[PDB]
Image 1 (cartoon, rainbow over the protein chains, first blue to last red):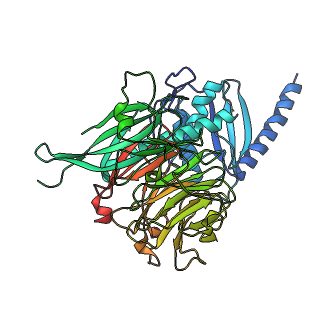
Image 2 (image 1 turned 180 degrees about the vertical axis):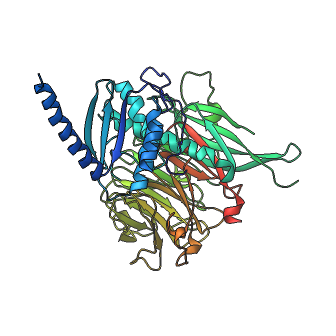
Amino acid sequence: FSTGEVWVNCKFTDTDGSLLDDGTKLSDRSVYNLFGNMSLYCFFRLFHTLYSRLEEIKNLEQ
Amino acid sequence: QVFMYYEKDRVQRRTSPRQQIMYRIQTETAFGPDENLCCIDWNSQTRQSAIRLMGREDLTMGTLKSDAEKWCYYIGSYIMSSPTEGILP
Amino acid sequence: QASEEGINQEKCINEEYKIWKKNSPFLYDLIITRALEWPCMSLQWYPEQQIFAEHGYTEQKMFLGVRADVGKYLLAVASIQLPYLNQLRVNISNLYSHPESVCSAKLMPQDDSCVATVGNYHNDVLVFDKESFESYSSASESPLKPKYRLTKHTQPCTSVCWNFLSKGTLVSGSQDATLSCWDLNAYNESDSASVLKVHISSHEKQVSDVRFHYKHQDLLASVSYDQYLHVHDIRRPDASTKPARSVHAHSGPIHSVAFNPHNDFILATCSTDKTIALWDLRNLNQRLHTLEGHEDIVTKISFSPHEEPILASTSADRRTLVWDLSRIGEDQPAEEAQDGPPELLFMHGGHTSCTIDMDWCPNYNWTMATAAEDNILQIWTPSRSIWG
């Protein structure tokens, strides 16, 4: 409640002076992000290993 | 709790810099200082994942492309009531 | 790449802004924010006062020197509304263009009409009087001309100080590390150098501040970038090269020194070493105390002309701190140690850049006016609750 509370909406002027984003413009995003410790990192690494191996198998299937 | 926060951010297909920054600081606070933080971005548009060790000098969003879009996006990060990202006190 | 840092920094400046703006009604008993035209290099409160009791306020006066632009260097007088206890605007006017720059403009204590002005752009001191302001006409194409031109230095002067008792006695410390005490009632039309009472070379680096005792003609202090305090008495004969004392006060370039108006024994000294030093004249071997709390360069300091234990300090981290020194050695709870040592009293950060300067309004208690680098003036007094 006291760590991430904004401390402005305020007008920012560009080189010409245009009002820019106060961190209040909700853009349309597609690239999501996640954070974690080393445990989830290692999980992800082993997971990609297994995925890549089965992908090679599927590519040989023909 | 970190997964709670990720679910909160995730379904929101739009989210301002601020809210992602509050998500970041919430997560870090739930974690602590001495656990090394890594990040994983999922780009379902080009379907690519990327693993990046985030330190105490790493900025939240790094794929900004224009110097005025720089202006807006990594202006936005220094809004947390916590101290700065990328600079060390 | 540097953009990112700059824009973040600007944004948290804005952040500090409305996070001060948001909780103001629980902190202060008065706030007047004024967006003047121009950057105000200095301010000095005026001791004369109007009291409109039936209307219900008081007006005080202010003297500003501002820059309109490069080379456009001007002066102005303001009237300031304070509310009334015993039973609301900031008005600019009296704008006269100056010949050159103003870094310090001091008015004589017992006579408002005179102002000694110097700037970072000239080594001449220009002292203005009644006629110079009143003979000027804003329709005229030329600026004013001061009462006198005082010139001994070869580098621009940093500040000046009148004698509060000695009638028409002034001092000027400059950038060429020299001092000059001046006496206007010893003029000669043939001798513009007869105003030169004394010139001193005691300092070794560029002087940042020279300033007299509040209750004494013959005592002044000088502080210089070589981390040294010098004590001068002008009626010494050897004072032209020998100071009365010389002390290693800090480890960085000293910016300013303030004399306790009530008590003739305490002075305060600020440096870029982010630490405020106290000094007592009977024990000069020893730093009296050190107040911490600014985490980059502190620039300038001042005592309260109503109570001595209150000291104000301004710094580059956009804060001004007020210390009540009656809390040396006291106890403080665990959570009370967060904000700093217990002798810290108040902290104001409504600005958005380096505060230029301050001044106490001597007609109202607990009130101060601050001019900052972003063309902003602040009149503010905290609530009673913190000190009442």
